[PDB]
Structures are given as C-alpha cells and as structure tokens.
Length: 315
Length: 310
Ligand SMILES: CC(=O)N[C@@H]1[C@@H](O)[C@H](O[C@@H]2O[C@H](CO)[C@H](O)[C@H](O)[C@H]2O[C@H]2O[C@@H](C)[C@@H](O)[C@@H](O)[C@@H]2O)[C@@H](CO)O[C@H]1O
Figure 1: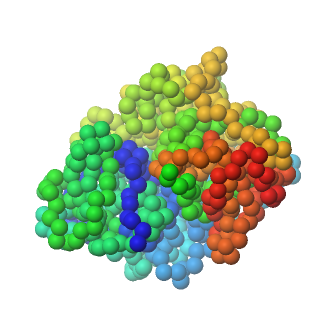
Figure 2 (figure 1 turned 90 degrees about the vertical axis):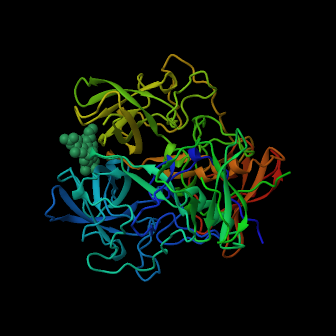
C-alpha cells in the first residue's frame, strides 16, 4: 500500500477550497450549533472527491454558461438569467450523482464578482475578432432563481443594459456583496440547488467530532466585501492543495483516523497535534473559539495511523 | 536520488501560472519574434522558484497595500496611488534578490480587476470594493520601488490609509492604446531603470523545435479581441516541482503526452531544466488532443536528442 502523505506547505502557502482566497488562520468554534456539511473542499484521505468539489482553484464558486435574457425581479438592480454548463463547457447532465455542477457555491449569501462575455460571432473588419464586455455582478444563492442543478441561475448588475443575450458568459467570484441581515449570509446553510422547496441530493456527508473534548479545526479565510460593515470569513475543512494532493496520491487509508502534528520548521518542535479523519476533516482537543495563534510558516506533518480511541494532547 | 515526476493532471485540471485562469489548450507559435522571458510560472525542474513566482494561485497578478493619494485623470476616471507590500502583508524589501514583489504581473497591458478594502478601525469595520485597472506599462507602475497606481470609474469612494487588495479578473482592453504585449516585461522600477534578478529567457536551441505553451484565454472589460496568456508550465507543475525538489539528472527531460484510455503516446516533448517545453512542430496554433491526455516523464536525455515530429 502506497504510504499516506500530506503536502509540505505552510499556512502562507495554502488556499481555501470554498472560495478563491488564501488561508489566513486556523480556527475553531466548538459551540457551533449548525450542521457542518459544506460541499466544496470535500475529499476523502484516499482521494475521492465528494459534493461539488473539483480540482481547479479557478473553478471554486465559478460559473460558465450563456445569458438568456434580462428578467424581472422585485429586488433592486438589473437581473439576468443565465444557463450554466459544466466548467469545462460540456452540458451539465442533471442525472449525474452530484448536487449541482462542480464548483457551484456551497453557502447562502450574496456572492459578488464579475460577469464577463466574449461573443461567439466575429467581425471580419475587426480581424475576425469578437466583441466583449464585463460588469460587476451579484449571485444571491438563497434566491428561488438560484437553480444550478436545473442548469440555470440569475445574477444582478449595477449596469442597466450592457449584458448580451445568447453569448458565452463567465462568472469570476471576488467576495460578498453584503453581510447585513437582509443578505442572508450563512456559511453553513446550503443553497437549494434545484430551487425553492426542493430537497438537495448527492451531498457529501456532515462532519463532527465524536470524541469528548474535541472540536473541528478549520482553515479560515477572510472574504472581501463590496460594501457595508463586517469582517466575514469562510472556513474550509481542508485547503485546496490538500484536495489536489489526496486526489493525486490516492493512498489507501489504513485506519479511520490519521494522526498529524503541526510543526514549526525553524524550531522543529510540535505546536499541537490533530486527528485527520478518513472523510477529510480535522479535529483537535481545544475548548475555545477563535484563531489558532501560531506562525504561518507552520505545517501539518503526517505521523501515523491511529484510531478513534486515540486521546489528543490538549492545545 | 529521488525520481523526477510530473503531476497526473489533464489539461482540464490545470491552471495558468501567469494569470488566474484554467488552461484552455496547448499552443505553439514558431515564428514568434519576441524574447520569451516571463517571470511568473518560473520554476526549475529541481524546485527552485525564479522571477516573481510564488505558490498561491490567488497570488498571481495580485497586490496588497494601502492607498495614499487620489489623482484625477486629465479627461476621464480617477487614479489612486498605492503603496504595496508583500502578499503576506510584510513590508517589501527592495534589497531582496527578486525583480518585484512575488506575484507582480509580468506583462505589459491594462489589467482589469477589483480593488477591495477592509478598514483597520472600528465594532465591525467598513468595507468597499470597485472595479479597477492597473496599467503595467505606466511610468507610475513601480512595484520594485514599493508603489503603483490603479485607476477606477468610481470617482470618490476609495479610502486612504486602509488595507487594500487587488483581485485580478482580466484585461481592460487590447486596443492599440492599451499596450497589451504578453512578452514585454514591465519596468518594475520605472522606465529608465534596468529590471533585475530576472528568470532567464527561454528558447529552443535545436532546429525544427519551438516552445510549447499552456494557453488560457483572458476576459476583457470591453472592446474587440480574443486575448490569451501563454505560460511555460501550469501553476500545478510549479507547486509539484517545489514540493518534490527531485535532482535533475540531465538538462533535458523527455516527456510523453499520453491518452490514458488507449495508453497511446500522442506526441513527445523536451522538458528543459529551467522549466519550459519544446516540441518538434513547424506550425502555429492549438494542439488538437483528446481531453484525457496528460504529460508523463519518460527519461533524461540531452540537448542533442531528436524529438519525434508532431
Ligand atoms: C458610463 C460608463 O462607464 N459606461 C461603460 C462603457 O463605457 C463601457 O463600454 C466600453 O467603453 C470602453 C471605453 O474605452 C470602450 O468604448 C469599449 O469598446 C466599451 O465596451 C463596449 O465594447 C463593444 C465592442 C461592445 O462589446 C459593448 O457591449 C461594450 O460595452 C461598458 C463596458 O465596459 O461599461 C459601461 O458601463
């Protein structure tokens, strides 16, 4: 059996698997009441991608498709419907056993970014080159019109008219539009992928500590805002480089729990230890919420396969 | 001696190391007259990062810093002077042996993106973001001196003295006046000053060979065009080589592009020690290849090895 390994990357060399952001800090929140069941950044230790997880950092919270038409919506702004394909441009087949096209956002909120278009049709006078446009845009993932599993979503723009029907369209995510109460930001609330009143399917399972005294450990990034007050964050279970590494290696999991040590390169010492679980998440023995205050040159080193009855040294 | 390897990734699982884009096609252009000396996506086969190359996909063509002054354009828009730090927030030290802060763009053009800010002071801090353009050919583009300028359509709502992020999205224009040239380096310290600490230029040295690129198409804010950015190796290869740091056993690795389903080799290429590919091809344009194909290391060869024609 191929030996299990993690990449050798300090925190400052890792990126979030749930939004295109660098990892800023490690983080715990033991008293979290929500069920933790994110769909991006989901990969087993033996390399099986789950939920809506795909490998490209550029694909996380991205969409590709075509605008159909401007549409009416009660909310302010100018609204547009777009069909969505797979990120590789092939038609999304709703009979595949995934919750939504891979890369689809996995949380409730107003995702701010840029919609860009490059026309299919070309002009001989322009050297046979297509016309283009891009504009800031917001995708409300809690909207009844957010139906990526049905192959269509809606976005809104400040721009009132310069979005073209029937043309190839890309959404590049940048941040959140707002985190006011009215903007329904909740990182642990899944979108309804097929719309209002429908049940999501094919989900990666929820994650939780099972051993007393343990809590989830997250890789946290702070997410930009278009406006308003706030310091919002997105917490992932494993960074995108771990997803990429595990997928590559596909090493057999020799037990249900790997023991890992967070180590300082300069000192050589272990700052704390953690359980890395088979389904792809970490727990630590810690009784507080907030950041883990440690150097960003620190990294996780795989020590050995253990089991659920292993007692972690307290942080 | 740790064996040399490449990741197992299809084109559809790779991203560009010079701009945050997926790889769209493999590409050649034998008649290219420009010197190819890009500074992002530069890594030797034994894992030495060069130029302005760093590991984060989010760091490519990114900046961090603080705005210091608003300067109105003569006719339209507003410019903003920005002091830049390293992407990790530490102060940029110009005496370090790099051309510019890691992640700095490595080409001439109008780079379009979003400037966002989260204030230091507060119980929750204020935020704003706006579309922005950074003209990397501008005399005000001096990242090696710790400062740049960006322009916005927004005329007032950018704050001074507050943490600022640039997230790149595409190009503003590729019209004549927008000076897009993917192989022209910016003057990192301004026009009268020589760039320093550069990753070396790359070229075939054998007749009949040409560079092989990983090409991505880059979005446009407006106008006509179908611009592309070509990298020498994808970001995932940079990350892999850095991790492995396998000893290079000659100056040229032979790699095969293979179809996993049929197990057949579609073509072979030279992967040079300095971190770039050549092939024996006498035409320009995309390489047409099955979607399941990827490069596999075969063996070390030398500069005199003759590639099978494509
Ligand atoms: C008030 C305002 O800012 N309106 C902008 C409008 O100016 C933008 O249109 C672009 O403007 C640049 C200015 O140098 C050029 O004129 C571009 O050609 C133009 O983009 C237009 O390009 C043609 C070929 C079509 O593709 C149009 O759909 C496209 O708008 C636009 C787009 O950036 O944004 C408005 O809000």
